[PDB]
Length: 150
Ligand SMILES: CC1(C)CNCc2ccccc21
Image (tube, rainbow, N blue to C red):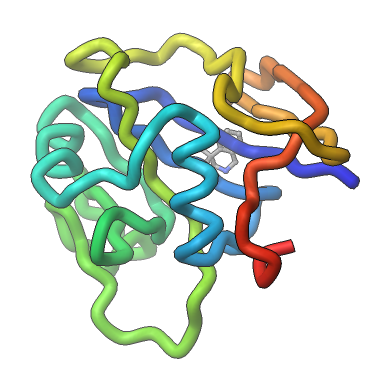
């Protein structure tokens, strides 16, 4: 009963969260997960500021209202060479990664490790935050509030 949450640097308080290293988060689980990080889904404006601070990924993830990939550098295999906040227009499917926004974060690039999920609740799941440098923080708990997600 174990969940890995892969997280990134924060950029103006925005970071990327990838569940179990695969597209596997629904829109409702996304909201709950950001809540567990005392965070919210970013707005498009918040994402655009993050991007300007140096944030890019090669993964689809939820923000408030859309599924996007922030791109700085054009790369053929990431959002088809687009730069800027690329918006997913057409897809059959509903599960992606998520982005989260933490207002308490530093204003620009913060590439320190994440070492807590301060707002997770009581539960049976071993939840592991995995940083990009491999550093890990684990705790027993739960964050999903929708039965359909469990
Ligand atoms: C950069 C990213 C999301 C890419 N997929 C693997 C992984 C693992 C730990 C932290 C971050 C990542």
